[PDB]
Length: 133
Length: 133
Ligand SMILES: C=CCO[C@@H]1O[C@H](CO)[C@@H](O[C@@H]2O[C@H](CO)[C@H](O)[C@H](OCc3cn(-c4n[nH]c(N)n4)nn3)[C@H]2O)[C@H](O)[C@H]1NC(C)=O
Ligand SMILES: C=CCO[C@@H]1O[C@H](CO)[C@@H](O[C@@H]2O[C@H](CO)[C@H](O)[C@H](OCc3cn(-c4n[nH]c(N)n4)nn3)[C@H]2O)[C@H](O)[C@H]1NC(C)=O
Image (cartoon, rainbow over all chains, first blue to last red; front, top):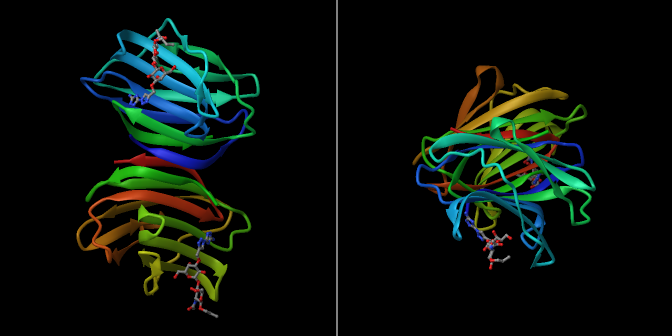
């Protein structure tokens, strides 16, 4: 369990940027965003080799403790042993996740949060910088 | 309040850099660092006009919920309505706080902390970036 931040007050349209080091032997890492640990509008989980999955981004939500319907992306712009930046914004309909190598995708916003107040990082990613719009 | 962060895992000699916006109407702002909210190795409180002080930085510690004795610094390189960066490092004996315009001071490490895991901001300072060197 890595950095946890609360009271972020990230409003629609504003950008959260996180830069970190992906471990040389990384298996996976997680960024969680939402209201608190039980209420995540985005669970962002690049899996290098975890849960039987290789080089796959897994995303989901968590609402009142309940995991939503998982979705997988088809591009994996991360390497073990490198620096990576992630940029996230949102509006009421979607979160937009921008990643290295030009890749961007949307994830439906399934919760009803006015602002994103909570971020937690976990796994094989050493956070070097966080910037809030 | 403002941003609260935990699991910072800051170790001796490492640098925590915090950049933010000092509000236009600033009276006072606070950056708290320590083990947790009741165990602060540094309560860093620039006062523009507050609690009986004008353009003075007040520092204190908090040990098991109990405030220590305040120390008043001799410099004040802050202005309302501006951006500011504060850089903090610590060791066995002291915290070193680097401020805008080349100023710095030391504050004794009264709790003898070997790691800083908690930070919180309050008042007229909106955190825009946090970085780890
Ligand atoms: C839909 C179920 C089908 O089988 C599997 O069931 C697993 C759960 O029983 C699925 O894994 C979870 O997927 C969740 C997202 O939908 C979360 O990723 C969950 O892990 C939560 C977690 C991660 N971490 C963590 N700590 N550090 C790191 N790097 N990750 N701690 N807690 C994973 O345990 C796993 O994704 C899923 N597989 C598929 C293909 O969907
Ligand atoms: C008639 C004078 C009585 O003496 C005063 O007594 C006050 C209350 O104990 C002293 O203030 C506290 O000093 C503490 C450090 O020793 C803390 O600064 C305390 O405020 C807690 C606090 C402030 N903030 C905050 N957030 N944002 C801002 N701007 N401030 N968050 N938590 C302040 O309420 C204040 O420093 C002290 N001043 C004198 C000169 O002794």
